[PDB]
Length: 315
Ligand SMILES: NC(=O)c1ccc[n+]([C@@H]2O[C@H](COP(=O)([O-])OP(=O)(O)OC[C@H]3O[C@@H](n4cnc5c(N)ncnc54)[C@H](OP(=O)(O)O)[C@@H]3O)[C@@H](O)[C@H]2O)c1
Ligand SMILES: O=C(O)c1cccc(S(=O)(=O)N2CCc3ccccc3C2)c1
Image (tube, rainbow, N blue to C red):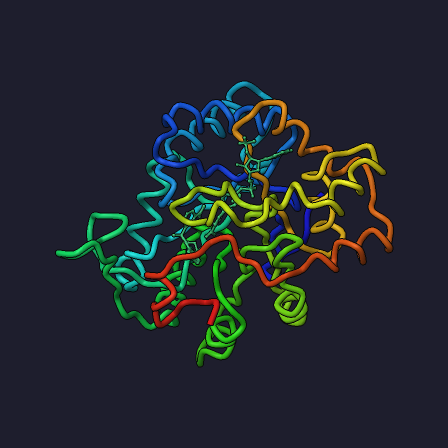
């Protein structure tokens, strides 16, 4: 249950989302990541940003040590945080991610966001007032440093996240390009289905990986809590009842049937296990059309600061 990437590697089509907000104790990532592997997840999505690479890495190691899986059966992703875009910072950031997870390699390393931030030790540098401080970096040079990380074998594959079509074209048309990104990891669910970007990615043999495929964690730091709750949608709920499944499973199956690799975050043992049931049923062509019709140009992620970033991907 994987897709072949444009570099010859293979990515499992269902991935586990490991992000939890800062209020969650760190020991939780370790617990739930083991649970996810135990349920059947083989793709595990982490990032510098998430401040959990130690614990995710330890969960991976634990399931290798206990005999359940081999290193090569797990697809582990991490990501370069936006304070580390300047090229000289990229390999050391990857090496630090590796040290924390205690892995020799990541299966995938992504540029987390095109919205470069001021370098330093803070995740979210802010000035005098409360304002997040931006940087300016030619992301083509960040990409070249990513290429070097694949060539050294530290990342098997390299890709990007939160890129729009123009930003993907920039890399695709870089003079001297060595490796195309294998994927673009983006917000994608039935209220923001990205069909036009999906078609573009497919035209270039770039996989679209969906985040917030279940409608996001709706944390009020990023998401308006009066936005509509994806999983309460009436159409997804009628489909769930028809198939004897749940709205979440309908949302995840949708993505698989359109050629999207889909992530699913849950820190609940029963929901983690429910989500692997996505492989157990199929939606009809008419089911897919109905879900297609939910699209409403809604990105849950919203930030007045980021909206002013020159590399803001939403316009
Ligand atoms: N590249 C980026 O910028 C970026 C952005 C966002 C996300 N991501 C990645 O994508 C992963 C997932 O996206 P996300 O964090 O926004 O969460 P999500 O997958 O959209 O999940 C949203 C909420 O759905 C709930 N849930 C999960 N399975 C369910 C089910 N079977 N039935 C009812 N509810 C269910 C979870 O709550 P519970 O824990 O209570 O189950 C979760 O908090 C992240 O963890 C991260 O790895 C990347
Ligand atoms: O990787 C994630 O799980 C995640 C969680 C919280 C924030 C971010 S972020 O700061 O990288 N960023 C995602 C892209 C985006 C787009 C529009 C508005 C806000 C954000 C936040 C990413």
